[PDB]
Image 1 (tube, one colour):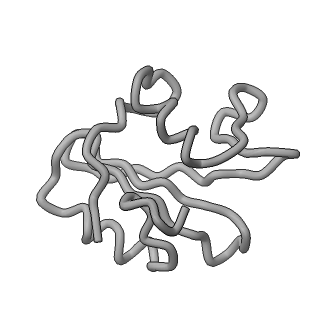
Image 2 (cartoon, helix red, strand yellow):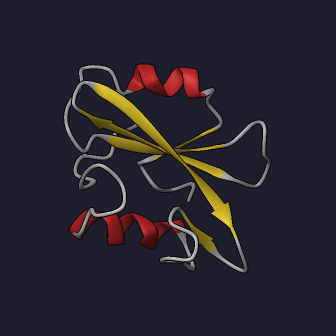
Length: 97
């Protein structure tokens, strides 16, 4: 959370595609969602495109229901820093400020 350099909180997606803009594989950040409150969107750069993955809540947290779920984002994040499978790419540099 707040003190995490990868978290930009409340910026339109629209902003994020921008932040993330000298493309660079695994360049990511995380922001709170608008249409569904309490929820997250993790933004990823991969192949010059920017992909997104809603973070759902289900007793906890996750992107692959059912698959892998977390206690903290600060931890889904770690997780997706060593094994990508599931999303397009391995998270590397957090975009920051």
